[PDB]
Amino acid sequence: PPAIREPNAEELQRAARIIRHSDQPDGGLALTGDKALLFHESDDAFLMYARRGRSMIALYDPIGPAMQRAELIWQFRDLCDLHHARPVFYQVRAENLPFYMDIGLTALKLGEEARVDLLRFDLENAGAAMKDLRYTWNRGQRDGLALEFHEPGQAPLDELKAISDAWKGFSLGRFTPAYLNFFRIAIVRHQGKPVAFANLLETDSRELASLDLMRVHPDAPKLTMEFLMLGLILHYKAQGHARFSLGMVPLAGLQPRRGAPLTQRLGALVFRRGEQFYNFQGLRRFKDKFQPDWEPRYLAVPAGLDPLVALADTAALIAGGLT
Ligand SMILES: [Cl-]
Ligand SMILES: [Cl-]
Ligand SMILES: [Cl-]
Image (cartoon, rainbow, N blue to C red; front, side, top):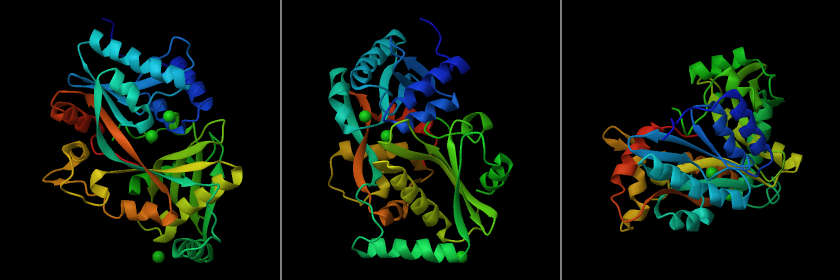
């Protein structure tokens, strides 16, 4: 069998095209180039993966049209058997689960993704949740916080490096010019001084927009984070987008429920930090400030086999990274 390689600049450009034609902005993580690309025979859809141990671990569901997604999943199983490796899918949607079942994979709960319904989101709606955001938006504007947007290529990357340094791989983006040049970038300035930034995952449609890197200067005001997020939500709402993703919160960050099946517990082993799980304290509570809708995300592993092995390889690949 041939060699698993990183994609070239021609392949990356082809992948970038596929993402634009999709409703899957999170596919933009393929553009770091540290993930191998499995293109459909039509070159209208791709799947991204990495190898760790005897496992081949795909990142997210395949990027592309519905039918091509399903056929890529079968392609991947074929490719995995050709290399004598076990297929693993990291952070997949429940709707694609039947396809993973068909190639002989079961699943473990990994966490939950928070997405804000932009069409329903309004700061003048009821509830104290909206009240607090109105305060954050005005109090923050008094204090000199301002959100700006830069087309791809723009934005002082030297000023971004300052925040980035004061503040990996596979499931995350990389602070490199080659990568950040692909995306729109939002910057928060405290009375002119850069205090936070974030690259923006978009598509040519307005179905979904999400996040990747989001780094904040440690000396920045407390509200900078909340302000930056709220600003992005209002921004994409105005642009006419339907949903905005705040990212995922792994199991340990959700409300603890023991007495639960191992299927909905074992997924925690992906995020271990020494003698402790990453607890992701307040991460759920923070995302909940914007009243998002939560949806499960799964880790697809070979069925009828001890998932501890695939969990180990997945844990190693992730190396503790999250948005
Ligand atoms: Cl996702
Ligand atoms: Cl999907
Ligand atoms: Cl402060």
